[PDB]
Image 1 (cartoon, each protein chain N blue to C red):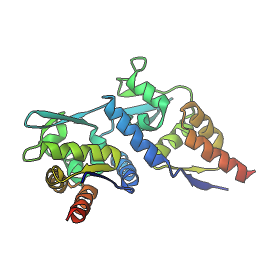
Image 2: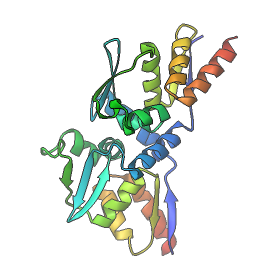
Image 3: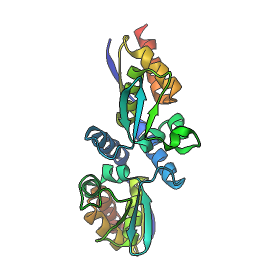
Image 4: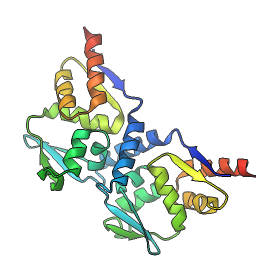
Length: 125
Length: 125
């Protein structure tokens, strides 16, 4: 009588739970820094939706093991939006911030955010 | 012109990413044990879908600071299914294992699994 059952709302509920844990400052295990600005996160969450972060945290230049990692290559504002996306599946865009977000999304290999930025640009033009 | 966009596929892709990281043995930060059987996991994933694990890993219990935690009273077979559900949104049930899985889901407050066990048992009879 063996049968497999699925819970279609589970991935959404799990994502919401991850975001409430970050907001409560709980179980965090990395702080990414851009210049002097600090971005706390869960390595496993970022690794699960970006092959860039996955490579960084599961191999790496001895940064894989660090608790505080200086991130080069994107703007601080871009990184802020990308992390908030990882925990929410959403991004809030305007023409002032889209350069930062889109550049960061390409660099950090988060194609769904690239596509959302392109949708925004079609509408804003 | 300011607008929020969402990616409906993100929570599903993220869940899949978490599952592949557990399968590769990557970024794990807890081992639960039942009679010396080891169950590795990511605390933040278990905490994001069970109020029991969230209390254990974020609270003032002695367990909150332990990397290896003994789960007294809990079914080892049941725990296996519960953790696999956390990472997959699925459970595979039959009449041989369902009692273990239901009992562990109730104890560990994995509420969707309780419902799925009840649905299987209602169908089986």
